Every structure is written in C-alpha cells, then in structure tokens.
Amino acid sequence: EDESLSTNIQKTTEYSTSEQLVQLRIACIKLLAIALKNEEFATAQQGNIRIRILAVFFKTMLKTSPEIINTTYEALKGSLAENSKLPKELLQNGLKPLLMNLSDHQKLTVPGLDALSKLLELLIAYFKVEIGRKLLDHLTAWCRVEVLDTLFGQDLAEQMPTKIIVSIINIFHLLPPQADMFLNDLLLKVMLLERKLRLQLDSPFRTPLARYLNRFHNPVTEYFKKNMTLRQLVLFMCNIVQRPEAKELAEDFEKELDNFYDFYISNIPKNQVRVVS
Image (cartoon, rainbow, N blue to C red; front, side):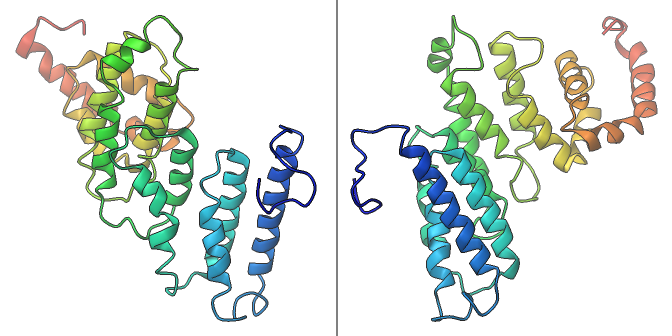
C-alpha cells in the first residue's frame, strides 16, 4: 500500500495485480541489467550510480517469489563480469540481513536459503568458513526428535522441515573449497536421518548430497575406501553414483574397482563371519 501505484491499490485485489507487479519488477531488473552492461552509459555516470542499483539488486534477493530470484541472479551473473573493488560498503548491507537470518533464529525459510545459495555462488565476504558450522548446528536443530515426531504419520515431500533440510544440504554445495571437515559429519548425519525415518530407498535429501559429493569427490573416495565394512554406506554410495547429478563421481569409482577387490579379498579371512556382506 505504498508508492508503486496511482489509482489501483493493493489491499482488496489478490493475484490480479501481484503477477503484474512481479512482471514489472523483473522487467525493470532486466532493463537495469541491460543498461549496466553498456559502458559509459551507467558505469561512469555520477560516480556511484551503479552502486545505487547494485543495492537494489541485493535488496531484491529477499522476495519470496523464485522468479524474481532467478531473474536477479541472472542480472548479477551478467553484471558482475565488470567487477570492481569499490563495492565494499553495500556488501555489509546487501547480504547482511540474510546472514543475520542465518543466525540463532531457528526459523529459516526456503526462498531465503535459495537467495542465500544464489548469493553464495560468489567468492567474497564469506572467506571465513564458519557458515558451515552454523549450518550444521541448524541442521542438527532441524533433525531433532520432537520435530521428526510431527513428521510421523504423513508423507515426506510436502512437509516444511523436509524442504528446509533439503535446502540446508543444498547450500553445502556452494561452500568455499577449503579442507572440508564437514564431510564426515554431514554424511553421518544424513545417513542417521535416513535411518531414523526408517527409509531404505530413495530419499528427498539424496540429490543435494549427491551434488555436494561430486563437487569435491577426491576425499570422498578415500573416505569410502576407509569405510567399506558398513553396509549402509555401500548402499548409500551405490544409490548416489547412479544419479545424473554425480557424473564425475561415477568415473572416480570406475578406476578404483580393483582396490575394492583387493580390500574385500584380503579382508574376508580376517573375520569370516560377515563374508556375505
């Protein structure tokens, strides 16, 4: 009910003006991106006028509509080719409400984490990899027992904690490539969450974990070779590799079958009680 209109108010009309408003917002975003792609037309005019619309581009990554999010992500990835150091103040104001939403609030949203991923496809302002610790803290606080007791009795694809956990696992894919000490914790937590929901087939959060695993995919082969006595890890990895979102983890396994052969052949006579496994 503010200055977007002249005579067509929005407190008595729904879906007749909201779609037109969304199309108007994405059209203005496309026009600003096309104008910003032109040199000396919006770049060197008035000094900081591209900063004034990059603040708009960071302010529009909090709308709940995914279409506006995808459009402004296309605008950012088309407009940040002409990057500069001079943006240093709006980064402490653009991605700041989302990172403050990420804190000890315990009520995260799905398009908020979607916009967090779309902003997380950059490499600046989160050089400290401590976002993963808060993400695992929120993941452990979303896979509790009391919230999973609300999951009892219904399905597992229309529930809000399932979508939140899927988004949390999904934004582990775009983390900075440091020494991922959150590999073992994340893998054990997803396997314990699958065992606690007692599902032994395809699960909702195996596709974001496959997108996490095929990205690094060098230490996960050694983590797999260090744990082959676990039946559930073998079933989990054999279901992950067949997914089309793990096209490079598949060829990482095809050149290591003989190591698996020598492992199982040399480890049969040590036990001789779990040979069928």
